[PDB]
Image (spheres, rainbow, N blue to C red):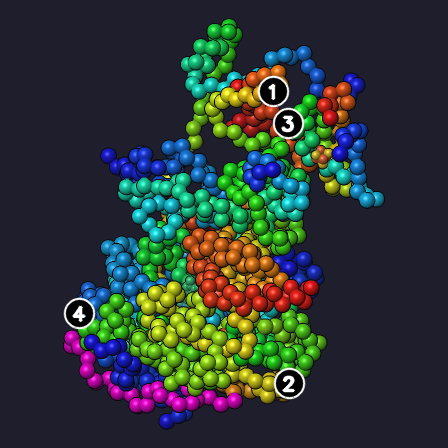
Amino acid sequence: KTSFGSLKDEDRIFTNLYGRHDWRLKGAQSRGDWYKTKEILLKGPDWILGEVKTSGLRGRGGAGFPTGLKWSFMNKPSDGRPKYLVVNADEGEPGTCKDREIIRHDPHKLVEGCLVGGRAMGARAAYIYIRGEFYNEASNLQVAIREAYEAGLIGKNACGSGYDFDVFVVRGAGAYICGEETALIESIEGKQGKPRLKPPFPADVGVFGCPTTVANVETVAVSPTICRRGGAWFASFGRERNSGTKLFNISGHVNNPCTVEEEMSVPLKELIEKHAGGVTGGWDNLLAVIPGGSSTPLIPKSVCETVLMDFDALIQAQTGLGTAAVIVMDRSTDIVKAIARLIEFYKHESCGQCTPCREGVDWMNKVMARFVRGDARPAEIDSLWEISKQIEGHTICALGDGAAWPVQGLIRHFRPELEERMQRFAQQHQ
Amino acid sequence: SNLIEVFVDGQSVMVEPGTTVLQACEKVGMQIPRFCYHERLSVAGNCRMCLVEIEKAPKVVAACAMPVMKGWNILTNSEKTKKAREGVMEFLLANHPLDCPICDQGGECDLQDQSMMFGSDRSRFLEGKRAVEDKNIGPLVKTIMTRCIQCTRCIRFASEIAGVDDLGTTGRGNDMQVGTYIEKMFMSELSGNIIDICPVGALTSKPYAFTARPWETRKTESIDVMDAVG
Amino acid sequence: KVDDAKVSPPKRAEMKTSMESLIHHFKLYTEGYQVPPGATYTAIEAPKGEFGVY
Amino acid sequence: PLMGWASTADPLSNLVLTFSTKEDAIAFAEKNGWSYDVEERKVPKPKSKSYGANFSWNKRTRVSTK
Amino acid sequence: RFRGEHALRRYPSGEERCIACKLCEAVCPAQAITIEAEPRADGSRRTTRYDIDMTKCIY
Amino acid sequence: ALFVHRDTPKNNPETPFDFTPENYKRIEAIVKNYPEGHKAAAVLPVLDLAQRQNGWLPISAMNKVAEILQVPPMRVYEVATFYTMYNRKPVGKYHIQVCTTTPCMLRNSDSILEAIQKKLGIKVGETTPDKLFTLIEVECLGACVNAPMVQINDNYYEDLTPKDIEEIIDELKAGKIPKPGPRSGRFSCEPAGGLTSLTEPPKGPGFGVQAG
Amino acid sequence: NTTYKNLQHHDYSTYTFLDLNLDLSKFRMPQPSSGRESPRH
Ligand SMILES: Cc1cc2nc3c(=O)[nH]c(=O)nc-3n(C[C@H](O)[C@H](O)[C@H](O)COP(=O)(O)O)c2cc1C
Ligand code: SF4
Ligand code: SF4
Ligand code: SF4
Ligand code: SF4
Ligand code: FES
Ligand code: FES
């Protein structure tokens, strides 16, 4: 053990991070794709599954379930219906910025990872569902899979197998909940964006009824190095409850915000200042922190001074852990204004199957608007705490839940500034 | 021989495998309230009233489309069951405006009965109460889609028994019309059978529309004529 | 009065403003609030005497 | 003919008696001495319909809209 | 707060304030209220016949 | 946003709209990707093709898609209502989509909005007083590490500021396209400061691998 | 080496995506059916 340290090189996943060295089939071959790969093909998917479940892999995408258990669901006995790997290439959750860089640099890593996943479970085909907002790099992915097509290396006779595995690309038609786990599936099907209930599972009934699995693109992109590298080398990165290098990115408000690859456990202040400029106006000039993304409550200063960047420790800090909007925001403007914009976002993009997210996001938007104007009474704001307690756990999907968390965190930490806002509005009305 | 144990408030009863929890709970007598499940239809997931707590669990499942696992023990009358119902019922009465005098299912709503028997005594939320321009369907069905609760029950009846595919959910967020996008006359057979199905006073009969009220009438057993079924 | 709208009608302001008050008003006057089953007996000292109702 | 009211010569046309069984219904009906018509308690059909079975692969049970 | 005469009102320079929603018969104890409600020509809902029996009304 | 059709001729079928047998070859590709028996998944890419074949899609486009793909049109109308590429009302040729919700407002999209506002003239959501500069602002796209950004039809403009605003306005008035590249320094998503990231040209395939 | 290796994508017209998957439709395993071609026949 150590005390979890930070990252040194060769613990990094791939080169060509930021507009750098290469992109071609020969660039990917010179960087390491398609190497010792048929010897992994002709070995056995139980070996791959044992390596996944031994490597301590945490499911990226804001779900927290380890991937090997989901893929152990995926080992249904063989029937007359194929099994599919769906690659969830959307970038929802404003802040995430995630696989736009992956598709901009190394699509052949995605080729390797979908090969690993479909070979891991008796699957037959893969479906890259990309965000429709990504047209140019979507056709970059097209040219790259064309390079793999004319490589004679994917599809029929992948390295010399009698086991073919094709990928098809479906673009987004422009939505947000297609990022989520099953409205994805019914947007593939031709129906409009509508999620599904739980007891028919994706591992049970998925794309048109065939069992399948939705996988995050980070987990897919890190999956071939699980095969071609040593046993649970990826597990030696953090704790033994969670493991792995995570793509910690600062969106938002620092000096020159950008993206870095790091290990699991990093001190947060050193993550901020040592990797994207620094906090503007001084470290004490901040207002607050959000980890996780657009669907994770805020964290104030004194909490995260001691609490560094860990899944379970942020659960202990009463939030979740997600990606790439691990940002501070400034004491200049108001997080009340920012969260009001966040609730306007959740209102303008959410479907309306479940009545609670619909009606609750309506009330919470109007009540945040009256907060920005300072209009209401404090009984209303604790009733807003009450309704946000009444939403979390009543939906199909989790977008209403992701609406419910930030207002709870704001009511926890920034109560008296809201009080002073309402007080000066009472003065101006007075 | 192929039955499953459940406990409704502890009481054991035996289940044919593959049914829903709601069917077993209305087998023993507990009329768990509902807004989109319908026995003569397929099952959507939009009612949200069907929530019920089951023990040894962190969260509350829907009882509408839950297959019966082995050895249930349901809390049909717990704290958070009634709290979840009070939640959902407080949500529904926001964007359903004050037309309960001028309704046509005024005696026979479902928001009425289930909000008296499950909901909240006082309400909240002054503003809001969005409005929708009423569409047209045909001169047999009067259509006020302000009172609609978007419960997706007319649609399943259309796309199963009618199959005509005229009704559609259009929009997102709050704004989600149940209607015909192109103002095409839904005038076919069984178009009169949709009005006993829309559980609020959104869809209603056109000639009957503003004449009487269910309490003043009385029922009488009778036989259909003019057709071979009766 | 009591603050239990499922027994008494609401006051007229909350009736004409909000929704649940209107629904409770309407079906409270039509349907009549449900009463749980059972028998009871009571009496007061009316100035005649033990005025009882069963 | 003066107000347009429903008037009738029918004293017993406002009756209903709530029971719990059929044997005591027949027993009381003949105990007071009149003829009578008995009907059926037509129970609903026992069904078992589910969400995933509505979302099959080959079967026509396919809602095409949700 | 005396109880008198049984008049129908109307809006301020407007239509009949009644709607024929039958509540007054639904709670009239002596049932002196008789309501029959056709909708009028212009689509809005209205009456035909709204009757009180002053013989029957218990005020 | 006025989702009843309200027929309004220059619409109201028959509206002139037709395809090419080469576009039929595209349709052959689309229903050859999807497995047989579940044809109704092609409504989304065929309506995508319809938008890239004619700028804003009319109702006759969707009716023709229903005529080809042998389904009644109401499901096609549903999918056209749900999604956010398909500006059903007639817009201009170019189309400004100022992506701004949380980090963009935080990094002065208000100056960006007001700069576009006072140089193009028109307000949010309005049409330009010609064609081909119809302005709206939209939700996040995915470059939250960047500045407030501008999406035009199938093209990005990232890392903006009011001088970049003046550039993009005057140069889309110059007919041609400028580059979609990240403007005003840091030519991709790049740490342009201390740069403690990876500094080694790549290892090659033949390093330490396992189970061979 | 700090060179922007991208902007090979600089030359995309409106038809490149559909036409790329069109031009790359061959060597295809035929996406197997299931009985009917639709809900109906
Ligand atoms: C609000 C919300 C937004 C989501 N956005 C995305 C997204 O942009 N990309 C994505 O891959 N999954 C998204 N998801 C789905 C989950 O992250 C899902 O777990 C993921 O696709 C696969 O995770 P796994 O690798 O652990 O299986 C979203 C889910 C929710 C609730
Ligand atoms: S919570 Fe809202 S967005 Fe999510 S499935 Fe339910 S209705 Fe749709
Ligand atoms: S349908 Fe609406 S207007 Fe009619 S009684 Fe019910 S809640 Fe009132
Ligand atoms: S119109 Fe009626 S049946 Fe249809 S969704 Fe609305 S409330 Fe339900
Ligand atoms: S029917 Fe009776 S209660 Fe209703 S509006 Fe008319 S007078 Fe009032
Ligand atoms: S029955 Fe309405 S959702 Fe379960
Ligand atoms: S909000 Fe504009 S980039 Fe995400």
Q: Nearer the viewer, mark 2 or mark 1?
A: 1
Chain under disc 2: F
Q: Amino acid at mark 2?
A: Lys
Distance of label 3 from label 1 (alpha carbons):
39 Å
Distance of label 1 from label 4 (alpha carbons):
97 Å
Instruction: Quadrant for the N terminus of chain F, please.
Output: bottom right
Q: Amino acid at mark 3?
A: Glu
Chain under disc 3: B
Task: Find residue F173 and name its label.
Answer: 2
Asked where in the image residue A398 lies, by quadrant, the reply is bottom left
Residue situated furthest right in the rendering: E13
Q: Are marks 3 and 1 on the same chain?
A: no
Asked where in the image residue A168 lies, by quadrant, the reply is bottom left
Q: Residues within 10 Å of mark 3 (few under 14, many from 20)?
A: few
Q: Quadrant of ligand 5?
A: top right
Mark 2 lies on a secondary structure that is: loop
Range of the magenta residues? F184-212
The residue pinned by badge 4 equals: A43
The residue pinned by badge 3 equals: B216
Chain under disc 1: C
* Location of residue F139 in the rendering, given as x and y in whole percent from the top left corner: 53, 70
Query: Measuring 34% from the left and 78% from the top, which residue is drawn there?
Result: A267
Q: Amino acid at mark 1?
A: Ala
Most frequent secondary structure within the magenta stretch: loop
Circles 1, 4 touching at the beta carbon (< 8 Å): no
